[PDB]
Image (tube, coloured by chain):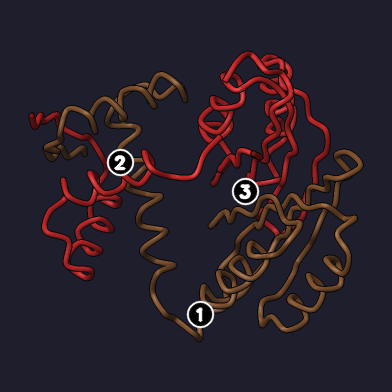
Chain colours: A red, B brown
Amino acid sequence: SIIRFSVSLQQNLLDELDNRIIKNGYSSRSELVRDMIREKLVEDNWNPNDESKIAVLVVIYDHHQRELNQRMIDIFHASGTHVLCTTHIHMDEHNCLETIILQGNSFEIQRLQLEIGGLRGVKFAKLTKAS
Amino acid sequence: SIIRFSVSLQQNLLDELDNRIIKNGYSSRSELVRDMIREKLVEDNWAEDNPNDESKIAVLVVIYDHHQRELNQRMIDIFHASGTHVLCTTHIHMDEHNCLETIILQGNSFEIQRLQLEIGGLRGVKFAKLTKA
């Protein structure tokens, strides 16, 4: 049984999507989304309230932001997740790439990527589950 | 300033979408789909064989046993043979038999993925995953 729902997005993202569909010969927009959903479904991945799960969060952000760093800290503290180690490299005047080694439970860790990614100043956020 | 297109899905795919929304704390199907589209576009972008585009940034995450004989040197050999530029690496000691390492790389997609492939296929390497920026 097939269902449909509509997706909202900006012109910029739609342009990039349509360009790729033409370029790679995707049959439709739905097809690309289906394939990615399937991909996420079958993708390598890691259970209880095991509080010993390890993960790595990768974050690219504008390090000029006066309060961004404190906000990330507060989000980790609120989540009850432990930061074992962090590394910041400045890639250019604007951008810092940070790797964050995390430890906590599965539920909490899986919600960090979106929280951090939504902070203003943050340009990229991607979590990796160590398993 | 917003556009909507329809997506047609088998129920089981929609279920996977909906399950992930709740798991990761997405606010809607639209937000998650946008995220997926972005991630997919990056993949396809990296899937292009652009030898001359050496501007790509990635982080390789590796868990390995530092006790494995010659593994360290073997990994060193691989990086020296690699055309990628290592910007920074951090090694953290987890326990006796587990070291976690994050490797920040720059180069073209061919070299970066060849590196991932070669490291991941090593004895003593438990885990190897690449983040495409």
Q: Amino acid at mark 3?
A: Ile
Cβ atoms under marks 2 and 3 closer than 8 Å: no
How much space separates mark 2 and mark 1, taking CA atoms? 29 Å
Q: Amino acid at mark 1?
A: Asp
Q: Position of residue A109 (x, y in %)?
A: 61, 26
Residues at discs 3 and 1 both on one chain: no
Quadrant in the rendering for residue A116:
top right
Residue B19 x, y percent position in the rendering: 36, 22
Q: Chain of mark 3?
A: A
Instruction: Give how far apart the Cα atoms at labels 2 and 3 are.
Output: 25 Å
Which quadrant does the C terminus of chain B fall into? bottom right
* Residue highlighted by disc 3: A60
* Sequence-first tag of 2 and 3: 2
In the rendered image, residue B51, in percent from the top left (x then y), is placed at: 49, 85
Q: Residues within 10 Å of mark 2 (few under 14, many from 20)?
A: many
Q: Nearer the viewer, mark 2 or mark 1?
A: 2
Query: Is residue B52 or residue B97 the one in the foreground?
Result: B97
For this rendering, which residue is in front, B133 or B66?
B66
**Quadrant housing residue A105:** top right
Q: Mark 3: few, some, or many residues within 10 Å (few <14, many ≥20)? A: many
Q: Residue at x 14, y 29 (%)?
A: A5
Q: Amino acid at mark 2?
A: Ile
Looking at the rendered image, the quarter that the N terminus of chain B falls into is top left
Secondary structure of residue under mark 1: loop
Q: Which mark is residue A37?
A: 2
A79 lies above or below A17: above
Q: In the displayed structure, would residue B72 be above or below residue B7?
A: below
- In the rendered structure, the residue with mark 2 lies on which chain? A
Q: Circle 1 sits on which residue?
A: B53
Q: Position of residue A42 (x, y in %)?
A: 38, 43
- Residue A59's place in the image compared with A82, above or below, is below
Given this view, does label 2 or label 3 mark the residue nearer the observer? Answer: 2
